[PDB]
Image (tube, rainbow, N blue to C red; front, side):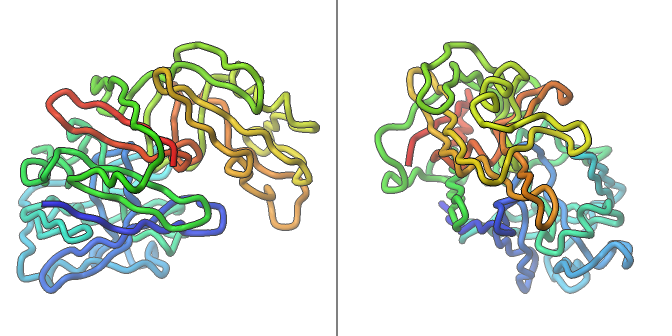
Length: 330
């Protein structure tokens, strides 16, 4: 089998992407944030504290003839931005782009933190990291991809995120019309539960490539590109007036600037992030200070190849017995 679904930016900055997902019988369609950095499929629901729902579409398990309470199971998750959610668990039928999994764990939120409530466009998350990170207790549950894998034509999914435009998540096949050149594959460590890999270096604008190993994760659920302080300083030093602001929480730059590109290495191959992809707009409405799309990882503990990086590429998440990642230009 295969599936193919369009993913759409939630706003004019590409802060995140939503993909429609059918849950239950009859289908209830929710728009979920596909997140290769986590491993829980959780939804706003009829169980979510009413004051914490503000415009999201909810899953109502009592209206699904295929929903079953997973007795005793609870979940609770916290994300790198400090947001969080928790609740109980149902199994139900879940379909993405025509690919159907029966018995998928659908984690129903009883509580969500303020940032989720405040984002009316995201009805939940669909995790695509390794199932060892799933938070369901006392019986850990599998991701949608892990459950679908055996049925897929090939044990892969691909992320083709757009810049200020829709893109595509495909399951079970590699669309050879969706990228240019060849796909360069690179080794993955699953030891931390992430799609963790090592970039071979970077360049800033038209500058020379610096060969240096950068371990990090391919994370569709993180907006920005978080890299070591040395690399980020080298980038922003090429932008007149750019500075790190403790009050804002990162590097800012004059909105009048034209930003240089940023290149990252994948083996001997190179992915170029255009300068425009690094502009996240005014720090507050009407400001002439703009927020940068490349930020230091120094306070995180891991480097994160988030959407800023991934949307410059066609990305293969290869879930073969030994997983690997593939990157192509597009």
